[PDB]
Image (tube, coloured by chain):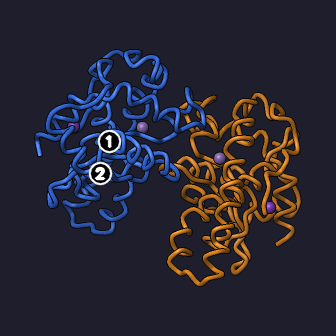
Chain colours: A blue, B orange
Amino acid sequence: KHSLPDLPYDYGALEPHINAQIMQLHHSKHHAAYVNNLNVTEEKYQEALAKGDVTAQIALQPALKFNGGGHINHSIFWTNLSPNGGGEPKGELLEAIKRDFGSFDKFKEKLTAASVGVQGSGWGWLGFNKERGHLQIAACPNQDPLQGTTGLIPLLGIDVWEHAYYLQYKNVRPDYLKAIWNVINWENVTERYMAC
Amino acid sequence: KHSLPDLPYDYGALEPHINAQIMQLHHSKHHAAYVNNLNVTEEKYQEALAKGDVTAQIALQPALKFNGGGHINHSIFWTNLSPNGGGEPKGELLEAIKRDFGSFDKFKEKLTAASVGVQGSGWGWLGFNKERGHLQIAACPNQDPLQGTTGLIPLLGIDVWEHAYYLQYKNVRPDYLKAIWNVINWENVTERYMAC
Ligand SMILES: [K+]
Ligand SMILES: [K+]
Ligand SMILES: [Mn+2]
Ligand SMILES: [Mn+2]
């Protein structure tokens, strides 16, 4: 059984970059729905697996991926943001970034392009390629989780589903991305990075 | 060269079912972007085709489908709605609906389920299967146009991208769908139906 994680900060803590209304809806409505559906889906999957119903297991894949991905992605997202975030990373993460992207700004540009370029709903990710030992940028459709579908270890995720910015930035996705850099919790990204 | 079609009614004509703000953004921002990108993409495709650059043609497919689909889908959508719409269809369309779905209400339920069930961004469609001679409900991801990807002739489309309802209905997609039935231009759906 999975559960909706508590937000490490107040809903209005990311003001004015991400308003309180979006944070409240995103967390208490969208994320909550993913968790509940995930639990219901894992429930049905245990039954199908117990009696060897292969057709049932395959029919459930879309729901498990979508809701499981939704839970995974958002849980990471909440920790990637902080009212005390922003600025630039320091230490080994900054070195790894300059080394694989040229500079911190070229990195911002690459991640922003990948996020703005998502056709439809999806996520822009900064991940770690364990096999090659270097950072890597990827985009995922809908709620497809980074690690489960590409093998990359997630470090920083940017949600570009319209519900993550529409109430405040309307259709101007680039304005949303420009603003989110001010609340990125580089301390958390560093932890995830040191862990792998 | 394609162009943004004029709206057959005022931006606030669908009040209170779909507020003026969404209609204005949806048409003058979202649809306009699709048309402009479509023109730019067809431009590049003519060049690649002229010099037989097969790699260029394949690299352009995502953009042409996404923007071309966006133009096609929305152009049809605007005509599917009307300040004088709502109610139930009459004539051959109502007979075809009762015949293939049991009743008008079972049809509403089926189309609503397909639209609410779209994981991520997409469209719910009521189309005509020319090979089997019957109505059919389908859902399409992102901006994939109905006819170009499934062969079904579109009759009625319901946009479930979050930008089509978030400002007014937030995350409650079912409320948006419940309300749109009040502005469906059954006269237009009937025309598209009689045409095939
Ligand atoms: K959990
Ligand atoms: K045209
Ligand atoms: Mn989200
Ligand atoms: Mn739309």
Task: Look at the picture and state if A74 lies above or below A59.
Answer: above
Q: Nearer the viewer, residue B98 or A146?
A: A146
Q: Quadrant of residue B129?
A: bottom right
Q: Quadrant of residue A82?
A: top left
Name the N-terminal-most of marks 2 and 1: 1
- Residue picked out by circle 2: A146
Left or right: residue A55 versus residue B126 is left
Residue type at tag 2: Leu
> Residue at label 1?
A73
Residue depicted at x 69% and y 49% = B105
Residues marked 2 and 1 touching at CB (< 8 Å) = yes
**Is residue A55 positioned above or below B49 on the image?**
above
Give the image quadrant in which the ligand numbered 2 is located. Answer: bottom right
- Quadrant holding the C terminus of chain B: bottom right
Along the line of sight, the residue nearer the viewer: A74 or B175? A74
Q: Which amino acid is tagged 1?
A: Asn
